[PDB]
Amino acid sequence: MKLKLIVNGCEAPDDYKLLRTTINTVASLRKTAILRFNSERLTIISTPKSSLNSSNNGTILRGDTGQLWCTIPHDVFRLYTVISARELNTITMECNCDSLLSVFKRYDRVMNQGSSSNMTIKLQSMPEWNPICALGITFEEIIMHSFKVPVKLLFRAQDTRIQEPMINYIQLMMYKLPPISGEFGSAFHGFIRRVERYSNVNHIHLMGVKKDDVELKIIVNELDWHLEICWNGPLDSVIDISVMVEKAEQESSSTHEVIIRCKDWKVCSKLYAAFEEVVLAISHDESCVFHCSLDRGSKPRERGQIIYYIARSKGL
Amino acid sequence: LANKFSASTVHLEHITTALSCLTPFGSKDDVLIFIDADGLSFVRENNHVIKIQLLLSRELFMSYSYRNETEDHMKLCVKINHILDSVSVMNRNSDDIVECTLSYDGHGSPFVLIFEDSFISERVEYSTYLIKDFDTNGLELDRERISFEAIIKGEALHSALKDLKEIGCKECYVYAKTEANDENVFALISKSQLG
């Protein structure tokens, strides 16, 4: 199950930034993350349904339902040697975010020092200890620094159970957020972080109303006084015992609303500050999806994708 | 606007100054708001013994609309702590705020305060409460029986008040006397720990 990979930060810094942001978000979202290595791309997944994550019982105690998916085209790695005997040569692993984040932080420190080396990653069988293997990582520091991280492989039955959430696209309203690098980036960044000024606020009500032809609002009713925050700047819109959640009747055909938690909003703000092209999709009283897209061309190349699904924190 | 009363301005100093002036009357109590074509007045009373009334005239607002017809004035009551907290959080970025508008739509509706920035507007609605039976007009100066009058400069009076406060003054006595040859004697006598 060879997984020899080469990572360089001096070539195509956008890809390195995307990988760093993905690992940072998955580490800040949950303790362990799933890594799928396909013949075409690398998928990094943070889901409460993972074997290691489900132990914490986050869903029933704190409502940890959000799911984070990141796709990294194989062009990011200088060398992509992924050979397997499964569908499309897919190898699934469940790694710990803390060790990987620490290793990448050390790599960032070394790169900022001035080194221009490369990081080599491989899958090895540690004799010290779903068999558990090690992710051997090596790199030079102008001195061969080598670190190893425990990892657990997943079977096909285990791999297929982890599926990306699918949203009702026809019943979904998408808004194209202003670019962060643009003149309106700072204003929107402040607007997203505005609700953080209220310590005791735990839920925020996002609303989007047609009539630049749409407007977005954040409502807070957890204080002694009703609070409404409106963005008046330009904003373009893209054109068992289980039961179905009850959806409140829409006030109008051109208004989409959803109540979510403040932590998810902070994560969305971090994602917006990380990437340039950001899209906010709202399914009325159902969910909120943050889609960050990185575009690179040569024969256009694969589009780097980061999708964060957030379930409603409360009903409407 | 469609509101019965709507007043918008570009100077944020008036609102904060009025709130600061009203603060010494208690951080957690009621404030009465009077609205009329002349302007908007804030009224507070303490222990039925003291009363304060601060008036913001029509000229202070860049736009002022009072479309009420049935009644010549509107009366409402709000909680000072709510406004204080809301303004304190909303006024953290005092440099960027460019417009401030008050609005009201008669009895049964909230008092609406909107801070409008270049691209972000924050709207807060304050719930209103029944006005206490006590009439603020009860404590008024009988203009036909003035015992004495005096005109003083603000800075000197402020310095005197600071001096009285810092010595822990407990009782105050305003002494006013006049004589011939334009001789005037206005004094404040304090009983405190110092004597």
Image (tube, rainbow, N blue to C red):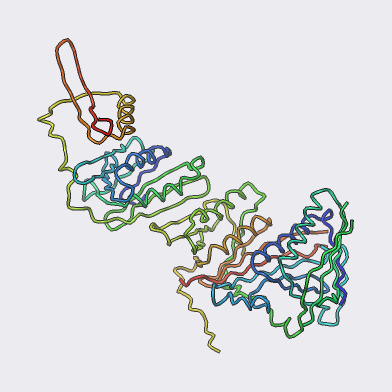
State which quarter of the image contains the C terminus of chain B.
top left
Extreme-bottom residue of the structure: A240
Please name the residue shown 32% across and 24% down the image.
B156
Q: Position of residue A75 (x, y in %)?
A: 83, 64
Furthest residue toward front: B194
* Quarter of the image where one finds residue A118: bottom right
Estimate the x, y position of residue B162 in percent, counting from the top left. 33, 31
Q: Can residue B78 be seen by looking at this rendering? A: yes
Q: Position of residue A262 (x, y in %)?
A: 53, 62
- Image quadrant in which you'd find residue B41: top left
Horizontal side of residue B84 vs A171, given as left or right: left
Compared to residue B119, the image places residue A292 above or below, namely below
Q: Residue at x 63, y 46 (%)?
A: A183
- Residue depicted at 50% across the width and 44% down the height: B93
Seen in the picture, residue B128 relative to A47 is either above or below; the reply is above
Judge left or right: residue B117 versus residue B86. right
Residue A291 or residue B79, whichever sits in front: B79
Tell me: residue A242, above or below residue B165: below
Q: How many marks?
A: 0
Q: Residue furthest top?
A: B181
Q: Is residue B8 above or below residue B167?
A: below
